[PDB]
Amino acid sequence: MVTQFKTASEFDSAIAQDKLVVVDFYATWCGPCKMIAPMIEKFSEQYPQADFYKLDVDELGDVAQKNEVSAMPTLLLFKNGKEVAKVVGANPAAIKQAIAANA
């Protein structure tokens, strides 16, 4: 599956003890930023153990600032309600391995 985040009250649970969650902090702007939504989902089939969510840089612009992620888009990894890695760019090369060694 795949979903986004509008309220921190949601994403807060996603990380909180729940394996490795791959949340993207795509910029509220940018052009080819929506084409990732389907991709972010395609990866959920290879790492079903990990949750593939998405962060809103418009609604949760802060969470994008807290982690210092204002790219467009960006990939954020979190283990057991904690962190693990951050690689701005879900280009077929890291977004896959990043979810392996981590999860």
Image (cartoon, rainbow, N blue to C red):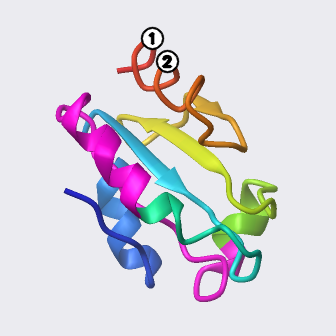
Q: Position of residue 14 (x, y in %)?
A: 31, 55
Where on the picture, by quarter, is residue 99? top left
Q: Element at badge 2?
A: loop
The residue under label 2 is which amino acid type?
A: Gln
Where on the picture, by quarter, is residue 22? top left
Q: Which residue is pictured at 34% across the width and 50% down the height? A: 52
Q: Which residue is pictured at 59% across the width and 42% down the height? A: 90
Residue named by callout 2: 97
22 up-or-down from 63: above or below: above
Q: Element at badge 1?
A: loop
Q: Position of residue 42 (x, y in %)?
A: 31, 45
Q: Between tags 2 and 1, which lies in front?
A: 2
The residue under label 1 is which amino acid type?
A: Ala
Q: Which residue is pictured at 48% across the width and 53% down the height? A: 23
Q: Nearer the viewer, residue 51 or 66?
A: 51
Residue 88 located within the stretch drawn in magenta? no
Give the main secondary structure, helix, strand or loop, of the magenta stretch.
Answer: loop
Q: Position of residue 6 (x, y in %)?
A: 45, 84
Residue named by callout 1: 101
Q: Position of residue 61 (x, y in %)?
A: 70, 79
